[PDB]
Length: 149
Length: 149
Length: 149
Ligand SMILES: Nc1ccn([C@@H]2O[C@H](COP(=O)(O)OP(=O)(O)OP(=O)(O)O)[C@@H](O)[C@H]2O)c(=O)n1
Ligand SMILES: Nc1ccn([C@@H]2O[C@H](COP(=O)(O)OP(=O)(O)O)[C@@H](O)[C@H]2O)c(=O)n1
Ligand SMILES: [Mg+2]
Ligand SMILES: [Mg+2]
Image 1: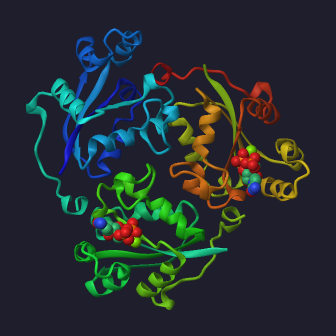
Image 2 (image 1 turned 135 degrees about the vertical axis):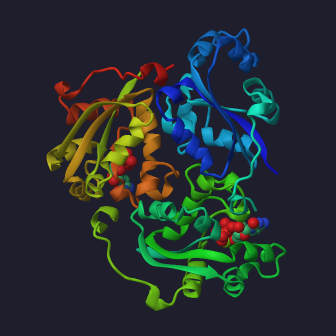
Image 3 (image 1 turned 90 degrees about the vertical axis):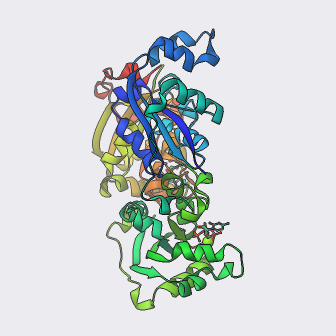
């Protein structure tokens, strides 16, 4: 039984030119790319993405940091919502475990490279916000017999 | 004092073509390759390898998954039995620490890439099962003065 | 607010020819190279570097192991003194977390590849011991807007 999570490379990931390295970390576990699109995030869409934080003092600067090119992605795998969170590491890179993306690449929470859904409910909401259903692709990985038990 | 451990790349490591990457992780610590052999594991040898699991319900499916090409290896180093276990990570890749082999490459326990001896006694037994003494090679690493205190 | 830490690649890092790999790990987080110098450490400077172990029985052998080529470095970043220590891992490689330099490269404390300052006071002292002020270079990373919040 597999699930799907929303992962988004933030403008710092694009500008630091580590997009390929990020994708490779998820491919390495046999996670399937179900969707992928480069766009430029805008305030209206970011207000919806960060709807839980409406009105909080840090939101305007957060939206400013996130207004830029992003790579929208959907990855599929066993327990991938929780596992992708573990792979990204703590929101604050200084607290993230060695071997995680944020510990290996970043310094501060406001520039922490990547977003991933924090729950099944958020994954559904975020995939619906950033992708059209046309953009989610169904296919099977040829190495499935050696990835899944 | 160094010791020797038995490490075996399972059929998923062969088929996903990550043999070299696995070997590089152990070489990176200055662990010495003392033996190495590609073979195809068969039910009779796997029954002996997994003798501790005799009679258990999951053993038939385990033998099925393991029937395939494997790379038998012996690595030598300080505390290498316990250290190789640490580097492999938890049996369940989803529970394994970031930076370990199973966390970095895998999703499920039944396809977790690699076996390693879990004790001095099992290392002795496993090395003897898969290798004849004439297959174990003794030489000294040229960088020993910079690896060992 | 950034700080500076003293990091030194020990003779084993030079001789095992992993200098570039070590530097890349710190560059990967957006830490700035503020100083760098290859030298051959002398007992005189090492006795001051290790002044805290004066009178201990292991000090003569520690100085012996360190009398050799070293790469002196200063890196700058947010919380970089503590973060660089986390990236290095525990003094004993066997106790270090996977994904740290010592766990990924080393076996024993006496050959643990790299030194890093352990506190603000020790960083200030160590930078002054190994570098003249004219050797510390001030410049801004072009990617600063995408590294710092
Ligand atoms: N409930 C179980 C028990 C075992 N296994 C499989 O059987 C192997 C051996 O189980 P065990 O010896 O308990 O785990 P490890 O020591 O991690 O395995 P290995 O000896 O292969 O390193 C596991 O690695 C896993 O592939 C499984 O899929 N489900
Ligand atoms: N018990 C010890 C303590 C230190 N050492 C060595 O001496 C160095 C300095 O010791 P330390 O306690 O200040 O540890 P670090 O801060 O260097 O990690 C270590 O990095 C090791 O090379 C050792 O080999 N055994
Ligand atoms: Mg076992
Ligand atoms: Mg110290």
